[PDB]
Image (cartoon, rainbow, N blue to C red; front, side):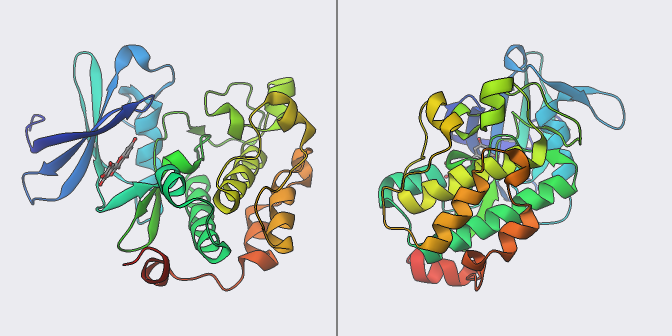
Length: 274
Ligand SMILES: O=c1c(O)c(-c2cc(O)c(O)c(O)c2)oc2cc(O)cc(O)c12
């Protein structure tokens, strides 16, 4: 028992998501990421089947961590007097999509297609497990550079999926939908599809389409890079001002732009010089 079943290594990063360190599980040398979150900085709390008070992030991760891929899995967690420590898997080598885009600029549509498809599969898995991420963006997507597999991270702004309206939100504003900005109300799926629209534009144009509230509310999409008509159409559809005018995940994946996706390994061999 006790939290010394892990050897601590360098700090990988730190921000609103806590402090994350590279580590190793001593029992079988497996790579892991160790996230530390201070209790005072956690606003949303839930409870596990057994009735213990834990961060919502732990509740959500447990719900999506059974089975396989698309989402980084929570392997274990610990409670300290002033923090919680989450043990997560550590693919390697890795780079998040924000950093990848910063370095390489706008992505070729074939690569954007493989990436976007994998994000859609991951988000669907979350929703099927009753989990809404609420902070889908490039920064929260890790790329396993060797396998070409994308993994969703940072469920610290998430919530249990529900069919009623959400009146609370603490994700990233520039990825938030017009109905949140104007009325402080949104439904889970349609808000998620809006964020996926921002993400897709971000991939093919190298930057997000909106910076100011006024731009989000207006919903006018200007393309700064050459992007195919089918891709523009999908983006504009995801970014419909009326939530009910947005596509379902099924409609997104049946869209003409999404056909003939590359498999993850092919994606890495062609685009991740792997
Ligand atoms: O699971 C995670 C993870 O593996 C990594 C990671 C892995 C690497 O191999 C790196 O080189 C690196 O910088 C980060 O970061 C994270 C950051 C989070 O906020 C949350 C996570 O769950 C992870």
